[PDB]
Image 1: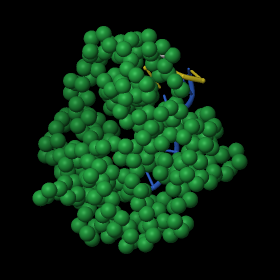
Image 2: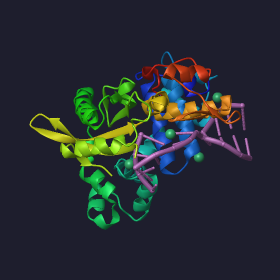
Image 3: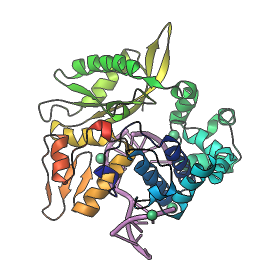
Image 4: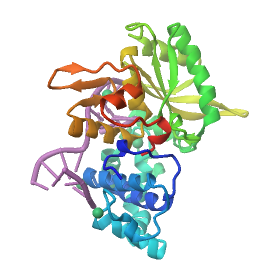
Length: 325
DNA sequence: CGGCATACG
DNA sequence: CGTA
DNA sequence: GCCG
Ligand SMILES: [Cl-]
Ligand SMILES: [Cl-]
Ligand code: NA
Ligand code: NA
């Protein structure tokens, strides 16, 4: 089992679901405490289990696996022996974890803001509502729409949304295309947001596109909230006899950069962090959603496809369905 | 020990 | 600071 | 927390 998540296929569903979920609780809790190193380790150990071809039933199966040291191994050991890990359960029922999870789930609220509110004694969404002077307009929208945004988006919803985005994009710039990215491109049947990448086949025609797209969607009454080339919005999505708020991200890239933007925005988040870490540390190349830079030659690799990018990094190609690290 | 992805709004 |  |  190779050390980086980008070196192994990771399917969306797998054979170690409970073990990985437990490790991810500890990762999440480390993040709430600002411990990014520990968050990464627990994320990586969880991902290794997702990549295994069968269930871990015995502690000896962890031998030789990367990212399993004393701590992650003890978590697995306790789950195998008793069905539960005392540390994980202590985190789950803790006021700190529950409140930081609740607050960071709000659109517009990150760990730092959540922690500040926690320290001020705030605990519930109604606590935040009672103090609107404490909120940015983005947070106010996140809080008003929190219930809808907590509901899973279905792939059927995604397809209806794509047609609407395509219509606006087509008027903004005929010939421009819309590609579904994010978790849905990785095969998810449900999700909490929808990501689209927009380009045009004629290099440079994409300049200034996103404001034209957003103005048109706003004119159609589809935008509940928006605040350039990336837009993090809340859209009005039809439902039987009503509608609901959905998080939608829109990103524009020049066609020259499209494979890099597609790769970046397809995720998963851990997959992309691992891939960029691999590129820099193992290959000495610097990867982002715009390109892949050789800092010695001072040149950019001109990729025509995601397959090109994997080849240039010396990695076996993984389709989006196997990037669920 | 140092390092942990890398951008844009 | 937030977002991915 | 773990790797190199
Ligand atoms: Cl840490
Ligand atoms: Cl980027
Ligand atoms: Na080990
Ligand atoms: Na948030």
